[PDB]
Image 1 (cartoon, one colour):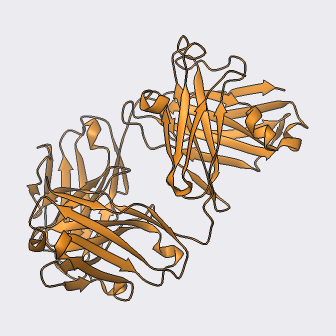
Image 2 (cartoon, rainbow over the protein chains, first blue to last red; image 1 turned 90 degrees about the vertical axis):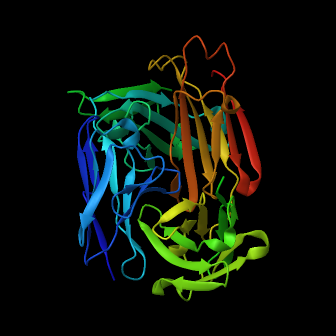
Image 3 (cartoon, helix red, strand yellow; image 1 turned 180 degrees about the horizontal axis):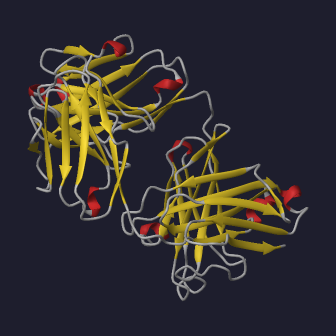
Length: 210
Length: 217
């Protein structure tokens, strides 16, 4: 067995920085192969024979190492480098991969653009009611959303989902859905969505009143 | 030129078995070993085994010996991998990669496999028009909520693909064996009530194709 350990797990660099990716096998390895994987796609050959760049890989990349310590160094992190890099070995058996290194872009903070959407009349017809809130294009991936129905916080029935860092501006977006029964929906008036982000001293709110 | 096209996403109940195919093209098929790799949702890659398309010989990762059964059909340059005794832990994305005496230089697009006891459900699509005005980010954001469907793969475009900038399709979230998904589009304020905005949803598993026009409330 030749277990490969990659570090760090998540790596954030500003464009132009020089980044070093490490891959440690618990036992001597002849060569190390590296792959790049971008969300929604299969992995792509990056480096073979521990230092050879595959077709299509820019010169800002360089692999290296010996025995039990290999690395992948990017001299000027560009935007298109954001992806997860995998190291692979076959000096021992079976064939193993490393846990991967996710490189994410570091950028200036941006406040999200909140939008709240009352239940569509089509949904109500179907005796259900879902109030949605979109917190878009913000940078510190960390954000806090809290729903309130008439001043009383509701942590029950909320569905949240986040997107991967955007390719065009390096920001994240979030979707917060609160689902209720048409009858429970109509037993209230004010619905509020409250985002808490580093870009503001006070919470960002969006509401509508029935 | 070199191309390995795999079979589509599949849904099967535990205890069943499936045969995923990996069609090779653009080279001499019998001259490269075909390897099968596994990617568990959120996790890392895990190697399954290889096959000599010339003599049908296989090498395996001990952990997959009783599960995968690698075969090849030289007649059409196709490589298969059957999975027996399926369980939830078998739900992952499966790839077929070609090795070239150093590394995996060509990979198929992968095959999403879902092993579940849940039943396929057509989605319910609801348009999210702003409440009597609202939105301001780059002036007026619209939505499209795709709710209560099960076969994960669902496709959402706006104006049949024409609207492509300002779109944020949110990844699905499994709730009680039914997924929920939502997409937004931030259009120019002089663009919306005036022009037609339609969110298109396609869910092959159930054969549904919904074209949902966003009208103001």
